[PDB]
Structure formats: structure tokens, C-alpha cells
Length: 504
Image (cartoon, rainbow, N blue to C red; front, side, top):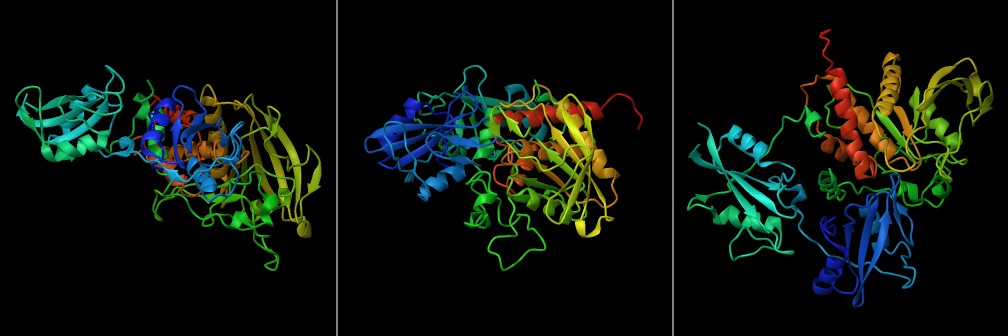
């Protein structure tokens, strides 16, 4: 994903593509203060064309193309020539050579968001002289600061700071030498050593690394923290051949959004002699940051739900002994369909293949509805099993909820249900394509669990958790808005649990 450039104006791209790329060269870039917007900068001949890509929460949407799960998948699709990308006027565009850049966004020493105060605190606390760190300058954006721990008392150790100016593209701490990137500069001095404002000569021997991530509560007073995860979709580009059989064609709500082959749910009891018949657009998601000795809920993430897959859906639930179903969308929102129904109306009794499901009741909240379903295989109507349907109904068609309390109740309830049950299978979570809202919900739920199971003194790495689920299903958590949402929701959950009353 080295073709992804964080801070890069549209005009500055044409400049970069024209001075370092060739016909076919392309790079991806953000819009900056224009949420839900990304742009693809292709170099056609000697011109630089731009295609905006929108993402309101369910998937990346390209203008003059199709929908995808991740920018990396989008690129790969067109790069494989799998389709025809075109622009209003200048039709048929081609992608050939990524134009790479070095974004430190994921550097072990990059801490940007950090302030000089929490900088000196953290470095002196580790006490080892020559431990460096870089951060965003609050004084003047675009320019960062080199903060290193020296070996002179001032008692704790004196942390010397250094300014890194960004003279339009290139970088400079003040010397006559300039640098391509932030990493080029950091590597340079890491060996050279660097002279400070005084005469003093410091060394960048080791980057600062923390671990005690818990009372995140303070981060709640992201854009970068998000895109920092972006450069990582490379690792999770697993095979999805199975969802590509011409047969399963009508089993996919979105042509290019498919389940990974290693975690895809396999419909049991099927005719092996029918090409593609054990297929369903859905994956098993687990908290893989836990060991076998550890305990925790597990999930199945699925796409919306077609009239063609309604019965296949019910087979998944039955075979998995799944007792709880979570819907994160209304059947149709703002005009576009999101998920056909798969349940009879209150009191009614419909059959979906070798199964009978009856809607024994409906209960409402301002935010959502709960349908208490009863299901049993026709060939044995006395093997009745209880399945509770949770359908969230207040999510904004655009963006994310204003407050987290609504989704937290939803999740809390869902959890008590699962827990109260004797040997129940994984929880089924779905929406439209099954990657944004469902990704967001499953993560929020996993982070809610380790806090609940272990204490308030545990590790709460949101990023690592999000990167972990993305390994099991492409996309999981789409926009920066959900990213922040996970944070704000958890923080509220923390305070809640951390209530004053010492009932413990």
C-alpha cells in the first residue's frame, strides 16, 4: 500500500506524477477535511487524471467503476485489468505502476500526536539515555519535533528537543542538508548523531515504545491513527477464490466484496456434486490475540442477505448452533436496499428449506428491535431451538451515531443473552456488505469483553484488535468515523464499569 500518500494535495500529485512517474503511474490519496473521500491519481500519457472514491460507511465507491472492501483490493482489481475504469470525459483509464512514498505513519519511533510534555515524561520515565521519539508540532502543523533523551541531569535526565521544518515537500531540522521524507531524516541522524541548539551532541540510539495502554479515556479530549492502519492491508490480502465461482455469482450482494477462503463459513450437508453449493458470503471471526487457554465469545460476519441466500442463511445459523443474530441496518435505507427480510411476521410461520422459523414476538427500544424467534427442522418439529434477533434501527445512513450509549445497550443485551445460554454457538453479525458497521460492532464487542473478563488494568489495543479482525474478513471497519466511534464507545464503557460504587 506504498502507493498511499497521507498528506498530498491533488495539485501536488500532478506535480509528483509528472516528475517521477510515467504513463500508467498511479497513487492513492485522501481529501483532507472532507470525510468519506479519497482520490485516485492516474497518469494518462502526460496528463494527470483524478478519480474520487467515496466511502460513507458500507464500502469504497469508485466513480465510473464498482464497489470494493479496501483500497488495496480496489487497486488489485483494476490492476489485474479485471474491469473497465473510465472517467466522464476521458473514458477508459489504465492502472500500471504504483508511485510509492515513505510514510513513517507506522514507524516504531513515530508518535506524532504526542506533546512535548507527555514526551519528556515518557522518555525520562524509561531513563535510558539516547532514546529518541518524533511528534507532530502543535505550534505549526506540517512540521514535527525530534525529542531525544540526553545523558545530562536536569534529578531525572534532560530531554533535548529539536525542530524539523518542512520547506515545501523536503525536510530540514535547520542544517543545510534537506531530506526526502521524515524517515530519511530519522535514519540519517540515527547514525550521524545530531548537534542541538547549544553545542551539545546527541544520539538517536533507540526509539520509544510503550505498552501500558488502558485508561484510553484521555485520548477522548485519529485521522492519522487511522491511515496508519491503512498501510497494512497488504498482509491481509488472502484468497477469496471460492466467492468467485460463476455459480456463487448470485450469492453475492456486491460483486467484489467476498469472504476469505480460510475463514469462510461452509454450509454443511450439501451436494458435493454441485459446483458451488456450500457457499455463503460469510466468515468466522475470533479474537486471535488470545491463547487456547483463554475464554471469549466468537462471531460470524455476513453480508446483507439476498432472496437467493435467505435459506442458505438459515442453514448457517442452524448448523452453527447460533443462538443470537445481530442486524446493523434497516432492510432499505435512503432508497438503497441493505438486506431482504428472512423472518415471518409476528405470529406467522414460514419455512426456509429444511427449517421452520416462527416469529414468537417483537420488543422495541428507541434504537432497536428484538424479535424472539423459534426455529426447528421440519423433519422434526419437536427439536425447537430459541434464537434471538437483534436489529439496530437508528444508525445514521451517513456517518456514525452521535453518542455511543445506544450501541452499548444493544451490545450489553446481546452479551447477557449469549452468556446466559448453555453451550451456544458464535453470534451472527451482518448488515449490507458486512464489513463496516458489523466490523465496528464486533470490535467494540471484543474490547468490551476483555475489559469485562480481565480487569480495567488490561491492555486495550484498539488498532491491534482492528488489524486482527481484518485478517479474517476484508474491510472490517471502513471509515475514520467508525474508528473514532470505537474509541468513544469504549471510553464510555470504561467509565461506566469504572463506576465509583465499590461493590467490589
